[PDB]
Structures are given as structure tokens and as C-alpha cells.
Amino acid sequence: VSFSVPGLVVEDMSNSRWPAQINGLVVRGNEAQVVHFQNGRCTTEGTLLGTTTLSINSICGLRGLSVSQASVADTTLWLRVEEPDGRPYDIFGDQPAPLGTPDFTAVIVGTAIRPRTASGAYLHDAYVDTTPGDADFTPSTGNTKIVLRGGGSGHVGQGHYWQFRPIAVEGGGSRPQYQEYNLPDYAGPTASNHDLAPPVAPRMPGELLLLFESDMPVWDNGAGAAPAQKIHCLLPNEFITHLFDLQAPALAEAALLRYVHPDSGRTLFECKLYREGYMVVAAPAGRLNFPLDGYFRFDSWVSAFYILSPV
Amino acid sequence: VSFSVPGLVVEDMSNSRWPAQINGLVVRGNEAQVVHFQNGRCTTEGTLLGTTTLSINSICGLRGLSVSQASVADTTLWLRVEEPDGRPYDIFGDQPAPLGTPDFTAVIVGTAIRPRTASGAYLHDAYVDTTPGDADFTPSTGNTKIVLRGGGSGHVGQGHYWQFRPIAVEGGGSRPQYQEYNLPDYAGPTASNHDLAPPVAPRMPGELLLLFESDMPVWDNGAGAAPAQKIHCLLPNEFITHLFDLQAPALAEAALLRYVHPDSGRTLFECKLYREGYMVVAAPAGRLNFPLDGYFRFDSWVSAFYILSPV
Image 1 (cartoon, helix red, strand yellow):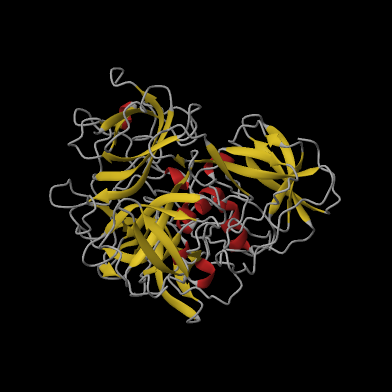
Image 2 (image 1 turned 90 degrees about the vertical axis):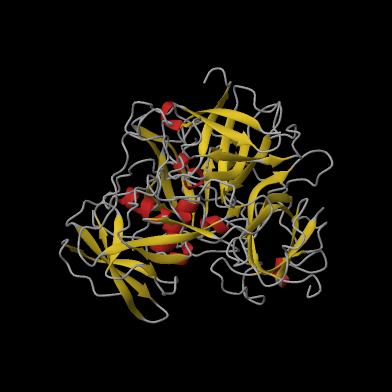
């Protein structure tokens, strides 16, 4: 099975850690805070890592049956978290948390949805505090607290299917910081994470990480004064489903991709997609000024010592 | 280029008319209301139709710069609608509306997001009325009205980028009906649609349309008593990106697909994926009781006269 990557243009592809179209290519330096994403992790052989799900609508989300607080105006909803496909979460499996689980610290704003209930469907404005300041964010041990913002009492009784779908993160001076490179405490403050997908840090001199950027919407209680945010990922969802479906074995350490721009009728830059599932370019940190109506094309398997042409 | 379909399991794939995982396979008879979807339309040769976009996060949404009402407590947002990629919408092109535009009539509840503006990012609870009752739904002529529910004044000034992201449809006695098979008036109640993707109506006797189904969340002002809903599409997004990227010529009228279930170690049913971009089965109308951890496999090109084994 020969290796290949999708021929879809960048602006048509979606973020693997957040529901947003890709609207930028940026290069990240070798910062103190190491990339350690749990979502959007796939090898070139199509091995999903961490909490990576192929189910796009399940990304950075939580889902499962409502339970009582004992068994574990704002109203708290308590979920027994499960996998996107409806099957139970394996506490002692080799995932840090259920697939799709948020992989960063912030207060994630979204909607709590109760879509199948016989008495009637229900939804409500909600948020999930994923920071260590929330002792109840413990999806690694089977439960999470979701806060229905300004209502929901009488609607959170046990025994019902719920989804939390993300819309934004909180911003503003009084509110907890959004830190996309800071992993949450999946088992809460009192216990440790386990089975994390490995850190991502380019080993070769001159090669810096290429990240796919999206806009991150911000909630600030109707003010509209908090500063705009972004969120990044190693690979678009379409790369991930493609690699998964393909299962091509890696013939070298990295796959040389060229970024082709039909309107220019030529290659704009080249990059290496390492077996471990991340891209690098020979370029300094910062935003790449290239049109996003171009696509990646697999040209060759190369060694780790293949020297990239400067971007 | 040989034809193939994705080998991904159904429960991993996503609705091409709505942001939701697929969670059902249903069969639809030949009712008075003919399937006429504008989203989720792609041929087996990878040709996109209607308003079908590859940008998953753009589906059933609106986006573009804010304009003044003149140029065209609740606060009305007026958009100059554009394409998902940021390029202008071609009023006199061959789409009924910009790509991803909602293709049914309802009141679609969602979030109006102003995510990049320098003075500060903003968002608010919003809705878009796509029924003929809203004369201001005219994306065919370049403008749509989005209603910010219970606020937003002072934030809707001209010259800013906005997105409306769908969450649910309204339900409950006093509210306009959700009709997923009823096309909207793209040019408003006083003008005609143009360039619609063609109707979907199986020609062969005994063959009925197979649809991929998802849950449709319902907003009913926090009551939680409105009946639960569904939404359907002809092909999941993962099929659509696969067909687009592939561009494989059709060799007959239809591709015989087998639904393979690894756990059962056998084919569960078969179907015909017509070139026009829809699947049929030899089965009566209603829900298909099959596990959704199976996948489709292309086995052969067949004539329209190929007789399907009953499901």
C-alpha cells in the first residue's frame, strides 16, 4: 500500500482539535511549553494516538449518560463519560480519557444537548472548566461536571443521553486563561494522567514545527472586548481520516511533501511529514504568508537528515 | 483512476447537511416531498453540486462582512454573504446560494460569531429564519438577516467578519415548523431560485433511497418539551471528500457497494450507489436495524438493471 496525502486545498480542511476551518499556516519555535496535543494525533501509517477520534463532531467534546451528584441560577450536570460511538469508556485502557475529550486548559463555552429524551428534546448554554481549578473535571476516572449557565434545573435528572458541544473559550481579565498547549489534569488534581500521546519537538537543527491554525472564538459575557484567539493542530482531520483509511507503512523516517499552488503553476514550499505525524519546514517562527488554495503532494520518502529548502 | 469508497465505519462519519455524527441508516419511500438537498451533493466522479462545500465547518452556515440595514432586546445583523474560503459570492454563477447555505426551511438557532475584529472578539446567541416568512433571507441576492436574540446592540456595525454557526432548530407550538425536505426561497419570497441540484427520486421499482441519519437538536426556549428531531443526507462528508479528491470516472450507472461488518465476519447487506450521488436498497421504508460499526466496500460497477438482494 503506497503512501499518499489528501489533495484537498488547505482552506477546505478542518482543525483536528476544534470545530473550525483551517485559515492559516504558522511555524512554531522550540518553546518551553512543548506541544503535547492529545487530539489530532495520527502517524503516517494511520495509527491514532491519545484521544484522537475520526468523528469530527465529537472533537473537544464530552458525551454520555447523566448521573446523580451523589453517585459521583447555574445547574450542574453530571455525565458518565463514554466514547463517541456510544460504547463505554475503558478506565484501564490505553487512552488518557475518552476520544474527543478536550486536550487543553480553559473554560470551554458551548451547548449542553439532550437530543433523544422521550419527554422532549432539551438544550442549554453551558461551559466546562478544564483547568486544575476544577476538581470535577475527571474524565479519566469516568465522570465530568458540566455547568448549565443560568438555568437547567429540573432538566438534569439521571438516566439521559447528553452531549457537550464546544463553541468558544472564555476570555477577559477575571476569567481563567485559555492555554492550548497546557494539558488538563484528566483524573483531576489528586491523580495522574496516563497513556498520553508523546510530546512533539523537532530534533533536527533548522526544522521548526508547521502548525495548521484556526480562529478560536471568545466568550466574554457579551462585552466584546476580550482579545481574539487562535487554536492549532498538527494535521487537518482530512489528513487523519485519509491516513487511517490508507494504513500505508512508513518506508522512511519522513515523507517529503510539496505544497502545490495551481494558480501559480508551481511548488511554493516543501515540508517533511515525520512518521510520528507532524510536519516541519526550514523556516523561522511565525505566520507563513502563502495562499491557502494550495494542496500537499507526497513526492518522496526521505531520511531525517534530508535538508529542506528554506521556505 | 479506479473507483473506491471510504472504508470508514458509518458511526465514525458525519452528516453532510448538519454538524452531527451519523447515528442511523433509514430507508425513504417515494413521498410527495421529493428529496432535493442542495448540501451533501456529489457525484461518484467527484463533482460537487448545489451548495455543497468540502469545508465541514461551513455546512448549514452563513458568513461574510456586516453591512448596514440601509444598504439592504433583539438586534438584527446584516451580512454581505460570501463563500467559505473568503472569496465573494458570484450572484450570477451556477449555485443557488453561497456554498454551505442552509437548504431547508425552519428557524435555525445558533451562534453569531465575530472572531477576528481588533477591538475585541464577540459572539451572541442568534437565529436565522429560513422560511418564506422571512423576506430578509435572500442569500441568492447576496444578503441575509441574522437575529441576535436578546442583545447585540452596538456590536453589529458595518465592516466586520461574521459567521453564523448552526446549533439547533426551533420546535414547540408557537414556532415555525422544521421541514428538512422543503427547500428555502433563496432569493426571498418575491423571486426565483436558480441552478438547483436536481431532485433525487429512484427510478427502478423495488429500489428505495437509503439515507444517513443524525440527531437534530431542538430549541424550545428552555422548556424541553418539544419532540425530538432528525436530519438526513445522501452521503456522509467523508464519502464526499473521498470522491472529490479521487475524480474516478464512472464505468456504469451504479456502483455495487457491500456493507461489511467485521464482528459478524460477513456482508450484512448490499446497495447501489448511483452515479448521481445517492444510494438505494431493495427494502421497504423505515429504519435499518444494523450495527453502525460496519463500512461500505465497492465490489463492482453495475447497470441500473442490476437486481439488489433484499436487505
